[PDB]
Length: 218
Ligand SMILES: [Zn+2]
Image (cartoon, rainbow, N blue to C red; front, side):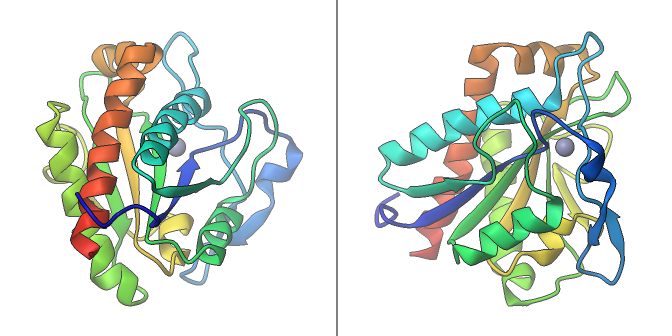
């Protein structure tokens, strides 16, 4: 898509490369409650961690966006130390007033279920959540599915998953979606996630979703 160079994308590779006791501290959810600052994240049965999958996949997304002239910033800068709380990741995104926010995750579900789901804030708390973020979720879902990655068989509908319990989505004031790429407990998704080429496969599809949404906003 044209007229996307110079637009701003905030990238959030879920979880931290290391955790301490401060991840249990309570932070606001955006709907009047609190939850833990951070969670360790899930892992494959044999211990490949979500935080490394999201980190490396996000680096691949960033490189492709840079090649398109798209500005990026990331919520964390390594995969071996503490990272920001879930409310802080939303605050970092909001401080940038970006055109798009993508948080990248991997899920833990029943081992026979595989595929992606795209989460978005619902019920919406502001205009970005009510309109553009819903459109972004659909474009992202379409591009993941067009890439041959099946929509999740075990949660959501057709790969879309309206959610009220994600602090980073609730607190965003700019277009924002969270991509659960697959189920780390499933043999196919875990094998893809453990491979550099599989992580590139997820990244390429996410980039198509981002670029398609950015182009639609122009
Ligand atoms: Zn996660």
